[PDB]
């Protein structure tokens, strides 16, 4: 269980390297600052991104507990 808010907050806690995985694992292009990457990742959420990427966010954030 989750929502379309925690994912954002969680993703917002991801680093550039992490964002690269989110985009890389999503296919999307990854190249820019964190804000730029975050915006891309965020747009992915609003653009609708499978729960596959959502899981990586939990794992990425988890390891960064």
Image (cartoon, rainbow, N blue to C red):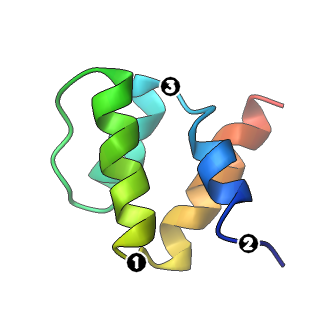
- State which quarter of the image contains the C terminus: top right
8 lies above or below 65: below
- Give me the C-alpha separation between circle 3 and circle 1: 21 Å
Q: Earlier in the sequence, mark 2 or mark 1?
A: 2
Q: Which mark is residue 48?
A: 1
Q: Residue 55's image quarter? A: bottom right
Q: Earlier in the sequence, mark 2 or mark 3?
A: 2
Q: Position of residue 33 (x, y in %)?
A: 28, 20
Q: Earlier in the sequence, mark 3 or mark 1?
A: 3
Q: Residue at x 31, y 62 (%)?
A: 26
The residue mark sitting in front, 2 or 3, is: 2
Q: Position of residue 5 (x, y in %)?
A: 68, 60
Under circle 3, the secondary element is loop
The residue mark sitting in front, 3 or 1, is: 1
The residue where tag 3 is placed is 15
Task: Please state if 55 lies on the left or on the right of 43 as rendered.
Answer: right
- Give me the C-alpha separation between circle 2 and circle 1: 13 Å
Q: Which mark is residue 3?
A: 2
How crowded pointer 1 is (Cα within 10 Å; few <14, some 14-19, many 20+) is rated as few
How crowded pointer 2 is (Cα within 10 Å; few <14, some 14-19, many 20+) is rated as few
Q: Position of residue 25 (x, y in %)?
A: 35, 57
Q: Residue 11's image quarter? A: top right
Q: Residue at x 58, y 55 (%)?
A: 56
């Amino acid at each position: 269980m989750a929502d379309s808010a925690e994912l954002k907050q969680m993703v917002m806690s991801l680093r550039v390297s992490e964002l690269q995985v989110l985009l890389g694992y999503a296919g999307r292009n990854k190249h820019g600052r964190k804000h730029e990457l975050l915006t891309k990742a965020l747009h992915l959420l609003k653009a609708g991104c499978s729960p596959a990427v959502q899981m990586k966010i939990k794992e990425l954030y988890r390891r960064r507990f």
